[PDB]
Every structure is written in structure tokens, then in C-alpha cells.
Image (cartoon, rainbow, N blue to C red; front, side, top):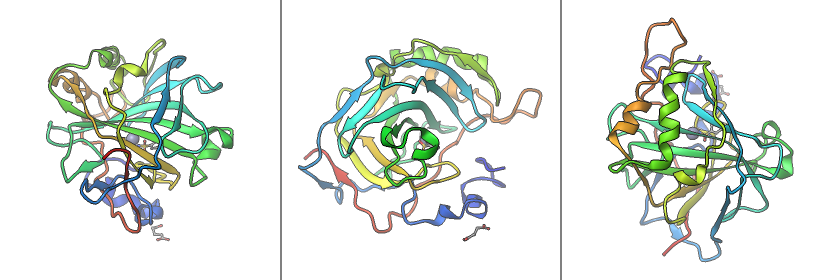
Length: 257
Ligand SMILES: NS(=O)(=O)c1ccccc1
Ligand SMILES: O=C(O)CCCC(=O)O
Ligand SMILES: [Zn+2]
């Protein structure tokens, strides 16, 4: 099965998922000088006041904080989007060292990690149908740099010991994802894909310009997770990021001057 090793990592994925070599793959490098300011782009509307987290899961590739998406409770609107997208889960990608870990890059800069808040377009009824559509998902990407701690991240950090290995989950209620957002909602946007198999070309990417700061201790706890299941040879969950893919025929737009 696919993963992030020499034998099964990103350079192998195309054999089982030929769309890996497609026309709208993610992530990409964001060349800040060639991204065009688009005055037609709207402010992003992030409405997470009623978000209901349920559970946290080690799926063997990352950990997902899952939400109740059975009603319009946590939604993303505006920005480049038409209509309403409902939050289903968030997860991160991160490195073995602070100098790598993000999927998107900015003028070739790699951040220590990247948060993905995943939302599906309500016009398709649920997530599985949405991923079959070119406007099915909106993923809000937020870079992490190492410095001061992010207080709103600590509840996530502290539960990771209980989901060390693949397949473990834990109740994770009342977590407020507003605590993971930076001050500014300035963003870049482009059409792309899931960054893990099945690599479907269904995502409007919205990447925030302003990173959040997390502490070295917080990211070190991410790096204690395991890709393996319980009682299997320990493989630390690090470097679970796909490198930048060819931009091909796409334009990255900026919401800000
Ligand atoms: N990593 S990502 O593109 O946010 C993603 C989101 C949902 C499913 C698969 C991948
Ligand atoms: O299935 C594969 O081995 C990848 C190539 C398939 C294709 O490019 O259509
Ligand atoms: Zn992701």
C-alpha cells in the first residue's frame, strides 16, 4: 500500500493512481511574484462558531480530527468559492526536522508543517460524492513555523499519546478549530487535488499567507506518532508530505496586494 517510504512514497503513487501525473495536482510551489492579485476575490468567510468535533484518528498517514458534518455547523464560504462547504476533518503534514514538512511551498520555502481544514460542497450531499466533482472540496491550508506555542493546539498535542499507532482513535469533543487560525485571512488560491491517494482533482485550494507559530515541543509530539500499527516495528510518523507538483496550465491568485 502507498505511504511515505523509499519503496511506497510519492514517486511510486502514479502506478496505482495514474492521476498522480495529472493536469491539476497538488501541492504546488507558490511563486509570490507571479501570483496575481485578483480584486474580484472576496474575503474568506470561516464560520466555525458551532463546530462539533467528535473524534481523533491515527489513520496510518496522519491524524484526523473529525467533525459532525450532518448539519450546516462549521462552514467555509466566500473567498473564491461559490456556495457552502462544510468542515469534515482537519489534519497536518509535517517533517522529521523543522526545515521541511509543508506540502505547499512559498518561493521554495518549506515550513515545518501544514494544517489542512477539509470542507465539502453541500451541493453534492456528502463527501464521497463531492470528491468526484471538480468543485467538490475546499481545503484551507495553514503553514506552521516553530517559535512560540499555539495555545489552541495543545489539546490536540496532549491526546496524541492515546493514538500512537495506526487504527487508534479517541473521543475528541468540544475542540474549537478557531484556535488554529492566524490573525489574517489573506490567501492564495488555485485549482488542485487531494495530496494523498486517490489524488482526485476535486479541490479549490485556499492557502493562507500568514503562518501560525507552534512550539518545538508541540511539533516534537507530532513526531512521536507512528505510521505502523500496535505491535509492529516502529516507524515514526514523520515526513508525511507530498512534494510540490508541476503547476502546468494554472494560475495562482492572491486575495491581497
Ligand atoms: N491532504 S488533503 O489534500 O487535504 C486531503 C483531504 C481529504 C482527503 C485526502 C487528502
Ligand atoms: O496504472 C499504472 O500502472 C499507472 C499508469 C496508468 C496510466 O497511466 O493510465
Ligand atoms: Zn492534507
